[PDB]
Image (cartoon, rainbow, N blue to C red):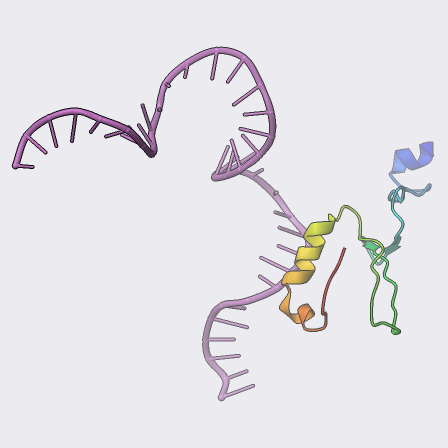
Length: 80
DNA sequence: TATATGTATGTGTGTATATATACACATATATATATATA
């Protein structure tokens, strides 16, 4: 590690924090991406969202999913 | 046609009760707006 401090190279990994977050994290190139969690059902055509990505408020997400007219053409009602 | 005469509003003081709003700054994302293509 002292050698790596002299030459500025990385040995031990330094990952993002996943504490108090139930979704999953992926590295695609030079960035990290954080994913939510849904639960598909065709018996009652209802998707049950169970988690949002990191630092996403809930009512701002719901109003953003309500304003977009291309997405509103497939939903009847959106309930919290 | 002037007069009263009983109506109705209306700020104002101290000590309380509960809220509201404009602006700067960076950067990533967004949802609709737009040419001209035709």
